[PDB]
Length: 132
Length: 133
Image (cartoon, rainbow over the protein chains, first blue to last red):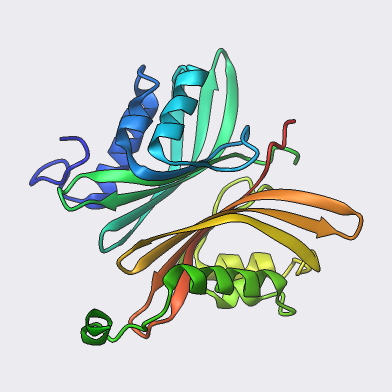
């Protein structure tokens, strides 16, 4: 499974976490990140007055926007900090949609649950220098 | 609490403690408060950076140029702390009152409990609320 450790591609937690994020970003299914998120997920992006709280609220939010994936993206210098059952992934992202780049900051926090799946418990998306 | 005893951890309300640390740093007279509260491997974002800050030395250099605190008054909105073993994820919104102006913020802080039972920031993400509104 893409979000579970194994003896091959998912042996190293940082490489697994980075691959998982890239796979969700490339998915045509707008539910991809929802399916990866846990029931207690907390989510921020630039369009929300305050953070979204809980998986059902996140699901409703993702359903409402119908966001296409980028035509292509570049994940720049992803860092994964691992602490017991938590992996903090941080990166910058150059996302291309219809011939324009949108540059993002991202923090994801993944938790290894008792069934050995890594699930997103926190997401924070922001623009790079939106006002300069 | 016997689990905390075997683990030599404090019998504290972790969410309340983490919220109190954050509020203290925000309102601190020491402009380097957040640098002191951060660990060597800290990663940091804010709306002025073209790419994320990595490492405490980079964070320190950045903070040396900032005048802080930026506001005497601020309101922390619906802080949530998710606790996972030696990690606490603090998320909140913050209304920061700069004299006559207000900046509305999103914030994610990740704190990690070190072996000495000190909670240190390993990740900070500050963003504006609805900057393109």
